Image: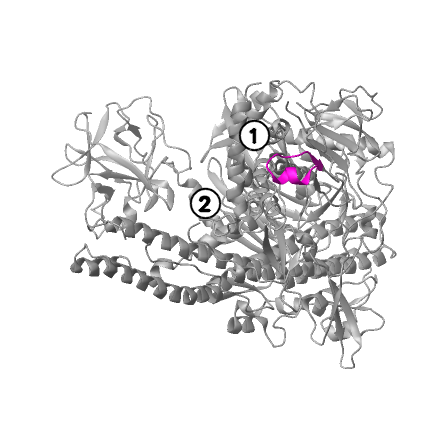
């Protein structure tokens, strides 16, 4: 669909390249059409002067007259747009949106006249057009939408649209960079309002945020169109059910559409299918659908993350740093190269000239009235109103599936038009001045504390006192709250200077451990509201409740409300409950039908009032909590930026000392990998802040806003329930006795209007962006997935970090413990895993676990699994009977640990953990902890990015290989072990699946080394364990049989018989004289037995007959018989058996 291969210098053709004039202005501009009725003009917008006065420059803007003036950049402009537009077409959602845009034409004027046309300079042709994409205007970091004719955009006729765009710049929000493709869609959807002409009047506005920073009460506002289109969480507080916010626009909008529908049904006959047929597609969609379109829909389609809360006032919350984009070097048809978090962008050079205009200055005065510091607070730049909207709003009582891309594609393009007059409305740019207040205080604000943690000097020192930092002259102090880090740095002032890489490693490790303990500190509080995790350092970070010894103690006594500044802001709205029924006829008790419908409505009216309070909580109470979250994040990053400088300074000094060039190279590599660990640890703290304040905000509703809603509604019921009693006395036809019944049946108690769910509010707080984050984060660097298939193997990593796998052919798949295992049957076979995370370094912590089965049956050393390079790293290999785990340091420190249990043809579960915060190493075999060591002396381990799995001569099975980026505990190991074995199969003593029609030997769990053998006492034949002297005797041989031949493996709850090999077939039967088991020579009398096992004894088995287990008996002379037991004097263990 998308036109391409169009570039600057392409000759004018009057078909795809034209020159047209801008409205009635005496200027022209080249144009290119990328799709039917869609155009792109690679120019700066004609309607503004690129140069403006210093007074009129808005906050946070960039101004540059030379941008997009040279043909060099002008050509790149066309390619960037085409890359994004084709990117949108990649998904069906984009096709519907773009297709609907192409087919949407303004209603022709009443012979008929058309508005959709761009006039050629010389008045000799006209080109159909709906959208025009220009370059940025005066401000090159803001996108707009401009309507061709104002009235037509509101009267339902519709009009042409113009869009501005900035494709070459972006900024990062939290972890990710913002995708420009989503920005283009936001401006495209807003165009549909203009073509359908459903633009609301400029007075249709809603409150958006309480400007709590100001001393006087003031509210910001947002247009209804912006709130609907922008998407996020806010619209969920307006678009409730039933609707609680109404205006004439909604009712008026629906009516006008029907009128043009009807007139069209007479217009269907006539000038050309290019128009008559085109209007049919426009009328297929209903206006209600357009009101439903929003960005949240598209983020799901493209899996694009974006800001979600107050995403139209971000200018107030934090400052934006810009980055550059290059097409197609960084951005292609599949979005950002390497994804939205790992894309490697370069800071823009235009960050140095952002216009700053504070909304207010906070001047901090000392005891002598001298300004210690002045901080700046910036406004969101939205419209402000001082009137209380909620107090003056009266809650009323009385009040893209069918796009069919196929049909639109077949519509012939417009060849000729009948131009209409006065399509061009004169454009005048809106220019506004920014005002500024000022304030004086003696108590620092949170913004004052935050500004004290920044600095410009490369040399400084952390201080825990706020007074010294601000009052210092040299500016060699910066405020900090890392108690442990400051304590450590202060305890080594007198030591000799660092001059050895070994001493550098020890210093670097202590800084990292202390920083992680300080930043991730939390405490647990039990509240009426749930369980809460309180961030301990919150008090000192921003000076909230910081006036006492402990922050957590104060928090419990005063509660969540104490954090915010403006405590009481609620206002009762205007209520209009005329509950009195409005008397004709109704002579019977069938009056109940009328009364019941009135009862139902009164419930809804109670709900809409409830939604009004939630919106007030969101706009007036949540807003102030979200502000604390942003400031707390700014604080964490500021402290992180200071630790990097301290580390950088130490390393730069050490580079001047007398250390080998090669050792310096490794120290540089180890430090670089540590910076990644600091960033990860900071990200944990940010997550702790979020949930801590989200639960506080939700909770203030339960204890503060909700009780007020009860009291206000308590009176509004006494006023309406009595009004229903009065009515039913007036009614005469019904009997008196029924009056008492109906009064009791239509009376509201407190229960009827009581709505609150702690869960149902948490669903509102969670956006789609939060779902993407939790659906894409894990602790696995490697998760091997194996799958046999017809003439095909599938071996790959599904961990989401896309490790690379390389394996030699002839690697076969075979069933192992719970799925498919690699079978390295033949010598010199190998498998490789490649990932950057496998280079460990000094600070990383990780874990590895897998299942193992060895068919070597030889006492010879052999390599198994290795990540060593030049005798630095770790490995596992065979020695003697068991395994050995080795880990070697750059300096030559080692740990060689020997594990003794391992022998041939058994299944083992091996799990290894490395913990650097505690300096602890843990090794598990199956269920039990084998080793618990301190690796305090190991320091730096740096090796390849490749892990190699190999054979020498031993055939082996491997299954479930996996690697974690964190240490594990005993509880996790035990759960994993038993959960994996909890499947439907019975197993042998060695861990393999049991089989029908295969020979075995039988052992009892109580006597694990004696096998059963046949004994003849009378003509009958019995079984018992061998005595202590005749142990040399050979055990009997058994087999399992199922009636259904061709069945191979035994599963739980299967029935069968037991057969003994010999010269004559024998089968097991239960004696009657005594409950001993005896052998018979007839398959007819053989007993049917049920097979089963125990969850916590995976490789053992049990036989059951009519719900009685088979077990051993107490000693009888020399024999312990195999019997059908019912006594309680025999141990429960005696009824567990093992095979082979």
Q: Which residues are magenta?
A: 148-162
Instruction: From this view, report whether residue 116 is shown above or below residue 565.
Output: above
According to the picture, the residue beneath numbered tag 1 turns out to be 795
Quarter occupied by the N terminus: top right
Alpha-carbon distance for marks 1 and 2?
23 Å
In the rendered structure, the answer to whether residue 1022 lies left or right of residue 490 reads left
Local crowd at mark 1 within 10 Å, few (<14), some, or many (≥20)?
Answer: some
In the rendered structure, the answer to whether residue 917 lies left or right of residue 647 reads left
Q: What residue is shown at x 51% (from left), y 60% (from top)?
A: 698
Name the one closer to the observer, 63 or 763.
Answer: 63
Disc 1 or 2, which lies upstream in sequence? 1
Q: Position of residue 743 (x, y in %)?
A: 25, 60
Say what secondary structure mark 1 lies in.
strand
According to the picture, the residue beneath numbered tag 2 turns out to be 977
Q: Position of residue 99 (x, y in %)?
A: 61, 27
Q: Position of residue 1102 (x, y in %)?
A: 29, 40
Name the one closer to the observer, 312 or 787.
Answer: 312
Local crowd at mark 2 within 10 Å, few (<14), some, or many (≥20)?
Answer: some
């Amino acid at each position: 669909n998308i036109n391409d291969n169009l570039s600057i210098n392409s000759p004018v053709d009057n078909k795809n390249v034209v020159v047209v004039r801008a409205r009635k202005t005496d200027t022209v501009f080249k144009a290119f059409k990328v799709a039917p009725n869609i155009w792109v003009a690679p120019e700066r917008y004609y309607g503004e002067s690129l140069s403006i006065d210093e007074e009129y420059k808005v906050d946070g803007g960039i101004y540059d007259s030379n941008f997009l003036s040279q043909d060099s950049e002008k050509d790149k402009f066309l390619q960037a747009i085409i890359t994004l537009l084709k990117r949108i077409n990649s998904t069906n959602a984009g096709e519907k949106l773009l297709s609907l845009i192409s087919t949407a034409i303004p209603f022709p004027y009443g012979g008929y006249r058309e508005t959709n046309y761009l006039s050629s300079e010389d008045n000799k042709s006209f080109y159909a057009s709906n959208i025009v994409i220009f370059g940025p205007g005066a401000n090159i970091v803001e996108n707009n939408t401009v309507f061709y004719k104002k009235e037509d955009a509101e009267n339902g006729m519709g009009t042409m649209t113009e869009i501005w765009f900035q494709p070459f710049l972006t900024y990062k929000y939290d972890e990710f960079y913002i995708d420009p493709a989503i920005e283009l869609i936001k401006c495209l959807i807003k165009s549909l309002y203009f073509l359908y002409g459903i633009k609301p009047s400029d007075d249709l506005v809603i409150p958006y945020r309480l400007r709590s920073e100001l001393e006087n009460i003031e509210y910001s506002q947002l247009n209804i169109v912006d709130l609907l289109v922008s998407g996020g969480i806010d619209p969920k507080f307006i678009n409730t059910d039933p609707y609680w916010f109404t205006d004439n626009y909604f009712s008026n909008a629906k009516k006008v559409f029907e009128d043009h529908r009807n007139i069209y049904e007479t217009q269907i006959e006539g000038i050309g299918n290019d128009i008559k047929l085109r209007l049919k597609q426009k009328f297929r969609i209903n206006i209600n659908d357009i009101w439903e379109l929003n960005l949240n829909y598209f983020s799901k389609e493209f899996s694009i993350m974006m800001p979600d809360r107050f995403n139209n006032a971000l200018k107030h919350f934090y400052r934006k740093q810009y980055y550059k984009i290059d097409y197609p070097e960084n951005y292609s048809i599949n979005g950002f190269v390497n994804g939205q978090i790992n894309v490697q962008l370069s800071l823009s050079d235009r960050n140095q000239d952002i216009i700053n205009k504070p909304e207010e200055i906070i001047n901090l005065l000392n005891g002598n009235n001298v300004s210690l510091m002045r901080s700046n607070i910036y406004g969101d730049g939205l419209k402000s109103t001082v009137d209380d909207f909620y107090s003056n709003y009266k809650i009323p009582y009385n009040r893209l599936d069918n796009v069919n891309i196929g049909v639109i594609d077949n519509i012939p393009e417009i060849i000729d038009v009948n131009p209409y007059k006065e399509n061009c409305d004169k454009f005048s740019p809106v220019q506004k001045i920014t005002s500024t207040r000022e304030i004086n205080t003696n108590i620092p604000w949170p913004i004052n504390y935050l500004q004290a943690q920044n600095t410009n000097n490369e040399k400084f020192s952390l201080s825990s006192d706020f007074v010294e930092v601000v009052s210092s002259k040299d500016k060699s102090l910066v405020y900090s709250f890392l108690s442990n880090v400051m304590f450590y740095l202060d305890s080594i002032k007198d030591n000799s200077p660092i001059d050895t890489d070994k001493k550098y490693y020890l210093w670097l490790r202590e800084i990292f451990r202390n920083y992680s303990f300080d930043i991730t500190a939390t405490q647990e509080i039990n509240t009426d509201c749930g369980i809460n995790k309180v961030v301990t350092w919150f008090g000192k970070a921003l000076n909230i409740l910081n006036t006492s010894d402990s922050f957590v103690e104060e928090f419990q006594n005063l509660g969540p409300i104490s954090l915010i500044n403006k405590k009481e802001n609620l206002s009762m709205p205007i209520i209009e409950i005329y509950g009195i029924p409005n008397m004709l006829g109704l002579p019977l008790n069938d009056l109940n039908e009328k009364l019941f419908n009135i009862y139902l409505k009164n419930i809804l009216y109670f709900k809409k009032v409830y939604f009004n309070f939630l919106d007030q909580w969101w706009t007036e109470y949540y807003s102030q909590y979200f502000d604390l979250i942003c400031m707390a994040k700014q604080s964490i990053l500021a402290q992180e930026k200071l630790i990097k400088q301290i580390i950088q300074n130490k390393l730069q000094d050490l580079f001047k000392a007398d250390i080998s060039m090669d050792k310096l190279n490794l120290m540089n590599l180890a430090t670089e990998k540590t910076f990644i660990d600091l960033s990860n640890e900071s990200q944990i703290a940010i997550n702790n802040i979020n949930d801590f304040l989200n639960k506080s905000a939700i909770c203030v509703f339960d204890t503060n806003i909700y009780p007020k809603f009860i009291s206000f509604m308590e009176q509004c019921i006494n006023s309406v329930n009595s009004n229903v009693t009065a009515f039913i006395q007036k009614c005469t036809n019904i009997t008196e006795d029924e009056k008492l019944q109906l009064i009791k049946l239509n009376t509201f108690m407190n229960i009827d209007f009581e709505f609150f769910d702690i869960q149902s509010i948490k669903d509102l707080i969670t956006s789609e962006t939060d779902l993407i984050k939790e659906e894409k984060e894990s602790d696995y660097n490697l998760f091997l997935f194996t799958l046999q298939e017809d003439n095909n193997k599938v071996i790959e990593d599904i961990s989401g970090k896309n490790t690379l796998v390389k394996y030699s052919d002839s690697i076969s798949l075979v069933y192992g413990v719970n799925g498919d295992a690699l079978y390295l049957k033949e010598p010199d076979e190998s498998v490789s895993f490649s990932n950057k995370a496998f280079e460990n370094g000094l600070t990383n912590s990780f874990s590895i676990c897998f299942w193992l089965r060895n068919l070597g049956e030889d006492i010879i050393t052999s390599k198994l699994i290795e990540n060593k390079a030049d005798n630095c790293g770790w490995e596992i290999y065979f020695e003697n009977n068991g395994l050995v785990f080795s880990i070697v340091d750059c300096n030559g420190n080692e740990e060689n640990i020997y594990l003794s249990d391992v022998i041939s043809k058994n299944w083992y579960y091996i799990s290894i953990s490395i913990d650097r915060l505690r300096n602890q190493l843990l090794i598990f075999i199956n269920d039990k902890l084998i080793a618990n060591q301190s690796i305090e002396q190991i320091l730096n381990i740096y090796s390849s990015n490749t892990i190699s799995l190999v054979n020498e001569n031993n055939p082996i099975y491997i299954e479930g290989l996996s690697i974690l980026n964190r240490s594990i505990t005993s509880e996790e190991v035990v759960n994993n072990y038993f959960s994996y074995l909890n499947n439907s199969y019975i197993r042998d003593i060695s861990g393999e699946r049991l089989e029908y029609n295969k020979t075995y030997e039988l052992y009892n769990y109580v006597f694990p080394e004696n096998s059963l053998y046949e004994v003849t006492e009378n003509n009958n034949i019995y079984l018992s364990i061998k005595d202590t002297n005749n142990l040399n005797i050979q055990g009997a041989k058994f087999k399992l049989i199922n009636i259904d031949a061709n069945k191979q493996y035994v599963q739980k709850w299967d029935e069968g018989v037991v057969c003994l090999l010999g010269d004559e077939e024998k089968y097991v039967d239960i004696s009657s004289e005594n409950n001993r088991i005896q052998l018979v020579n007839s398959k007819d009398t053989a007993k049917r037995i049920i097979f089963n096992n125990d969850i916590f004894m995976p490789n053992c088995l049990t036989f059951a007959y009519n719900n009685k287990y088979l077990s051993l008996s107490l000693r009888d002379r020399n024999y312990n018989w195999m019997i059908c037991n019912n006594n309680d004097n025999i141990p429960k263990a005696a009824h567990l058996w093992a095979l082979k």
